[PDB]
Length: 257
Length: 231
Image 1: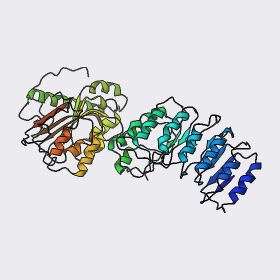
Image 2 (image 1 turned 90 degrees about the vertical axis):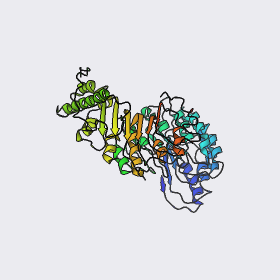
Image 3 (image 1 turned 45 degrees about the horizontal axis):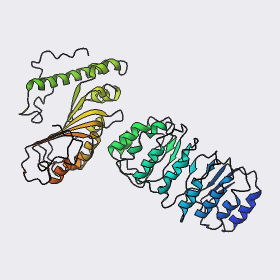
Image 4 (image 1 turned 45 degrees about the vertical axis):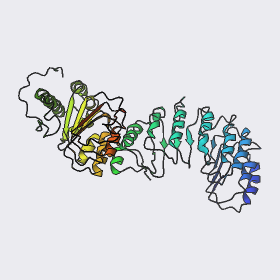
């Protein structure tokens, strides 16, 4: 079932949450470009995540998710084993989002099928990145990982550098970092991590506006060229000149903004 | 490649028209014409090796022999004269050009940047010389940055540059690989002086013809910050 940019009356979500209860064979659910709803989305998480089913992928994007809706899911993570894709990202948690995240992060101890975990954004969830590391290291199938829509400082890349030490997955392909606050001193600090991620398919590491030193341009071109795939990576928000774009190797696609 | 012995040191002033560097480095003091000629002779030797390579129509086939030949030598490049064969040498003969111990870049055409600012490798030690600089353009600084960064170790010699004063910290701050810095009869501001005293990974520092005397906190005040300084 796909619901893409469909306007709701803020009541129908409740009735659907009930109707969905009998769809015991449903496996895939997409909810995309939701209008402002508020109450009505929590009914989906209350009705679902229980009365167990075969849902394989739950992709609610930009769906006005509340911290309470996240808490409800956390409580209900004892159900829906076999679930592999859990999104609920591209979504800002207005209040107590970090608490809701902390509760689910310390769980998922029955969810052995989790891949491509995307996280909700809170102000400032960054203070808990180490809480993700706590359990991310326990999942050997994290082919994809997305940490989007928030400021990421030099301190945070050092924390991630520890994450990327690392006891290797040897199956990591997709890294999504939509924005950051990384200085010209690096960035570079985690370069060489790519040696443990030779099968990277794509990544972004995008920003608002940043002008890299020639040294960083050189390190990029001499590192990404050693990757097996590099299937259309992007560098959105990076001020590369014609001279720098000449240095960057023949990537399948290249985006600067 | 098996010949390491120099042999006869007479004449051989044909190569490298700037025999006395056109009034630059290696001037009145510390001449030793015998060593100057040796540098010229080895530089022409390296060029000969490159020319033999170019005419061998063996771009990669004979890379092993050329590696042994070039290893341990120095190459001099004039920024005002960069022959086409240098581009092919650096681009098509990897692990040999990089086997050179030193590359001397004596000055800023964009071509100089294009040659050095490549994605093939980082150079071991680069020796950059600045000479006829009455003005330092913002573009020139940008171009130098691109060149300075393409190395593991940087040696910089600034002689009689008038446009550098007030911009020395601006240039030096673009590359942390600097370990050897010399300034010959070239003025500077206190901010530039403080910057030099703020770089703690320097091994060599040489100041010539500085006539300011009253330099608060400067190289004449303490200079105890450069704990790694040997010369």
